[PDB]
Each structure stands twice: as structure tokens, then as C-alpha cells.
Amino acid sequence: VETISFSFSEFEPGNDNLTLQGAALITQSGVLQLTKINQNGMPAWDSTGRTLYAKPVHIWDMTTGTVASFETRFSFSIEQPYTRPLPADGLVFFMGPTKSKPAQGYGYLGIFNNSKQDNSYQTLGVEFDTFSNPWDPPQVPHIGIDVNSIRSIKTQPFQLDNGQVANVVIKYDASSKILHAVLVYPSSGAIYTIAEIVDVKQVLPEWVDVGLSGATGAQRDAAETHDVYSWSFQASLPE
Amino acid sequence: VETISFSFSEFEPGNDNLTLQGAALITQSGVLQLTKINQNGMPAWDSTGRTLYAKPVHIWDMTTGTVASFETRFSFSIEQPYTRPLPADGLVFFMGPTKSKPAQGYGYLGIFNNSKQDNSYQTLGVEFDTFSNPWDPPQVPHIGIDVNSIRSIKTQPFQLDNGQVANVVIKYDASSKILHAVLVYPSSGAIYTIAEIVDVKQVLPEWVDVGLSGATGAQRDAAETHDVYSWSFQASLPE
Ligand SMILES: OC[C@H]1O[C@@H](O[C@H]2[C@H](O)[C@@H](O)[C@@H](O)O[C@@H]2CO)[C@H](O)[C@@H](O)[C@H]1O
Ligand SMILES: OC[C@H]1O[C@@H](O[C@H]2[C@H](O)[C@@H](O)[C@@H](O)O[C@@H]2CO)[C@H](O)[C@@H](O)[C@H]1O
Ligand SMILES: [Ca+2]
Ligand SMILES: [Ca+2]
Ligand SMILES: [Mn+2]
Ligand SMILES: [Mn+2]
């Protein structure tokens, strides 16, 4: 059985097990800031940042025809300090081609180049979208399962607890091909769940990079924070 | 689209919207005790209790072939006061034939007569099993999805936060036929998730009773508490 597994109770500058891209930064206090925060403490607009695990993970194998089961957990907080305009854009957990660089920002969240449904993206993501683009449902924020497109195949509205930490658990069972994600707000006790069928074998390449990406709006002050406090990942490829 | 929906922030004695069977009792303080508790505050062994919603719900319809989507949420606490013998047996959220009476106790949790997988049982349950019977995996407690049998088709171990309150969310999506359940322990922040594919129209009858059932062990002190503090349910049948 081939297994990959990492865990971060917190983050520390320089940890060579993490690849930072764009605005992604690790404060001295241990928190990972995906998008830029000005020195006055306010989140900056027109910002995009991502963090990947330095090592690719074997998600499935052609020869044997088997696919791995995985689980990831992380905590984050989104703070929307401005009244107007509307905050943007959200953050995502994603698995895609190895050696990837940041794509388009804003509504694309740093992982897509446009709103097309294109299988060549070979990307899977679970988004926490805070801005309603023309391809989004009217409700925001919302959890969404993204398969080769920013236009989610499944969506679940949730209420933001401004500035509070949320716990996320994303799990994939190769057996039934079910991807189930859950979001919890310890502060209010709120629990959100979402599940959909995803055939990883038809979406992702055999090896993929796993990471987190966040982005702020395309206009002045259409921004919010995208802070991550911890992150763990585990995958098991049978045989 | 016929919809059924109820919610109990707390329980009140006499409320004719709930059917109590076996040992099930509602205290003056508003908590629902599925299994018996002696006057000295200790849980009694050899006890079985169930609570059914007083009205059947329409889960699917032959005519149209449409099946409903539902969601249920409840809070409970299991307290295992004795060191030995091992505590038993657990509690279940279940849907089954209407006008039913409690079945066998102990490991059968009051909803099955034996461990046989039989379609005539027409019972679906999400269990929180605290005792490992011959048909159970070695780990307890565990969440299990029961389809016409006490021998779960899917199992997920979880760590009991003895005596503390747990929040449960069980959701079923007719579209994908996915049953996803999540258990959360506010006290420790633990989050457990489990999901499996279940085709409700090949398992349950058109109309069903929805309820909660709990049971304590077959020998002295093989007992624990099975208290429920709140419970809500909702189902939507298209057309
Ligand atoms: O306001 C936040 C959103 O901006 C959208 O882009 C807008 C832009 O803000 C506006 O000035 C003008 O250029 O129209 C654009 C729409 O194409 C982003 O697309 C959206 O993701 C948010 O960032
Ligand atoms: O001890 C709790 C478990 O008891 C099991 O039944 C036992 C019984 O306790 C023992 O005295 C003897 O009769 O063997 C039985 C096994 O068949 C229950 O089956 C189990 O559910 C627990 O309640
Ligand atoms: Ca969006
Ligand atoms: Ca058992
Ligand atoms: Mn979206
Ligand atoms: Mn069991």
C-alpha cells in the first residue's frame, strides 16, 4: 500500500515541505495568509496566493487500475471588514497537475483561467466562494465541488461567521467514488455538509499537487482575509 | 411537492406529536431518555426504548417514481459509568414500516430481530454502536449505515467523549442517492464523517415511521446512557 501523509498543527516560516506562490505568506505568529494583508491590518484587493505540498501524491495508477482514498482537514477564517463594496473572492482546496503555477485570480480563485468546462484542466476542488459571479448560484458564501470547471457541479450555501475559525473535513472514498465535505463553526455550532459522486480516475492525472488557494476582488476594497491555521492530508493507494 | 417537517429544541412530557415505546421517557427537565435510568442516576441494563414521530412520512411514490430528499439533526450524550463489564449497546436513528413495535434489544438496538440481511425488514438506520457483536468490526463505538440489517454496509470508528454532548447531521440526496452523516463533539472539536450510496426505493416502503431507538446490555451493568436533547427532521417529495 502506497501512503502519503502530512500534518501541520501550525505553520512556521521556511518549512521546506511547503511551496508558497503569489501573495501566500506565513506570519511569525504561525498563521498562513493566502492573500495580502496591508500593514494597517486590512485585507488587500487584487491579491492571489497559493500553497502546495512540496511532494506530489500518487492518487491513482493505470497499470493496477486502482485509485486512492484520501482525507484532508484544515482550519481557516475569512474576515470581511469593509461595508461596501461586496467582499471577494474566496478560497479553495485543490488537486491538479504537478508543477502548477497560479492561474487567473478573482472568481477563478487562482486555479482556473476562465469559466469553461474543459477536461484538460484535470483539476478537482472544493471551494468556499464568497462572491457571486455570473456562473455562481445567487447565494454566497457557498461550498462548491469543482470538477474541471469553476462552475460547480454541486453547491451548498452556508452562513459566514465573520472573522471566526471554521473547521473543514474533506473525505474521498474510492470505493463508492463519494466526495463528502463538512464545514463546522465551533463558535456558533453551525454544521454544513455536502456530498457528490466524483470519479477521480477520469478527472485527475496519476500524480497531482495538492494545495490551497485564495483570492481577493478585482476592484478596490472588494477583499477579505483568507487565513489558514492548520492543515493535514492523508491518502492511501491500495497495493 | 409534499413536505413534512418538525423540530424540537427540547422535549416536553405529554406532547402527542411523539410516540414513546418501551423504556423511553421524557424528563421534566426536557431531556429524552431512550433507555432507563435508576433513581440513583445510574443507567439500567437490559433496557430498550424508542421514540417515533407520531406521523408517517412519504419517502417515495410508485406512481411518479419520485423519491424524497431528507435531513435530520439531533443532539445526544452517552455516558458509560462502569469500568467493567463493557458498556452496551448503542442508539440508532431509523426509518421503517409504519405502526411498528420495538424489535429485539441489545445489539439489535430495538429495530431488528436478528443479524440477517433481509429485504423484508424494510429498515434503514444510522447507528452509534458502542458494543462489538459478532457481526461488528472490532472498533467501538462506531457509526454504521444499516440497510435491512444490523450488519452495517459501511462503518466508521469514532472516539467517545464520555458523558458529553454530540451533534449529528444526517442528510440524504435523492439525486445522487448519497446518504451522508456527520458527528461532531463541540467539547473536543472532533468531527467524524461517513457516506454511502443507498437506494431508498429498493429498501424502504412508500410510507415510513422515523424514530430514535436505544438499548442497554444483556448482563448486569453492561449499560450506558442514551439521552437526546433535540431533534429536527425534514423531507421533500417532488410533486
Ligand atoms: O467586485 C468584486 C468582483 O469583481 C469582478 O470583476 C468586476 C470588476 O470589479 C468591475 O470593476 C468591472 O471590471 O467588472 C468586473 C466584472 O467582469 C470579479 O469578476 C469578481 O470575481 C469579483 O472580484
Ligand atoms: O455484555 C453486553 C453484551 O451482552 C451480549 O449478550 C451476552 C450476555 O451478556 C452473556 O451473559 C451471555 O448470555 O452471552 C451473550 C452473548 O450471546 C449481547 O449480545 C450484546 O449486545 C451486549 O448487550
Ligand atoms: Ca465566485
Ligand atoms: Ca453492536
Ligand atoms: Mn462558486
Ligand atoms: Mn455495529
Image (spheres, coloured by chain):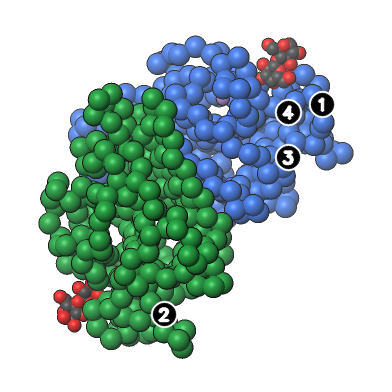
Chain colours: A blue, B green
Q: Nearer the viewer, mark 2 or mark 1?
A: 2
Residue kind at label 2, given as amino acid type? Ile
Query: CB atoms at circles 2 and 4 under 8 Å apart?
Result: no
Q: Are marks 3 and 1 on the same chain?
A: yes
**Quarter assignment of residue B81:** bottom left
Q: Describe the element under mark 1 as helix, strand or loop.
A: loop
Q: CA distance from mark 3 to mark 2?
A: 46 Å
Task: Judge by depth and name the residue closer to the eye, A118 or B154.
Answer: B154
Mark 2 lies on a secondary structure that is: loop
Query: In the current view of this chain or complex, which residue is farthest to the bottom?
Result: B40
Q: Is residue A90 above or below residue B111?
A: above
Q: CA distance from mark 3 to mark 4?
A: 9 Å
Residues behind callouts 3 and 4 on a single chain: yes
Q: Position of residue B87 (x, y in %)?
A: 33, 77
Q: Position of residue A239 (x, y in %)?
A: 22, 44
Q: Quadrant where the N terminus of chain B lies? A: top left
Residue A213 visible? The answer is no
Of callouts 3 and 4, which one flags the residue occurring earlier in the amino acid sequence? 3
Asked whether disc 2 touches disc 1, contact meaning CB atoms under 8 Å apart, the reply is no
- Dot 1 alpha-carbon crowd within 10 angstroms: few under 14, some 14 to 19, many 20 or more: few
Quadrant in the picture for residue B34 = bottom left
Disc 3 Cβ-to-ligand 1 distance below 8 Å:
no
The alpha-carbon separation of the residues under discs 1 and 4 comes to 8 Å
Callout 3, which amino acid? Glu
Q: Chain of mark 1?
A: A
Residue at the image point whose x is 34% and y is 46% from the top? B56
Spatial distance from mark 3 to mark 1, Cα to Cα? Answer: 14 Å
The numbered mark 2 sits on a residue in which chain? B
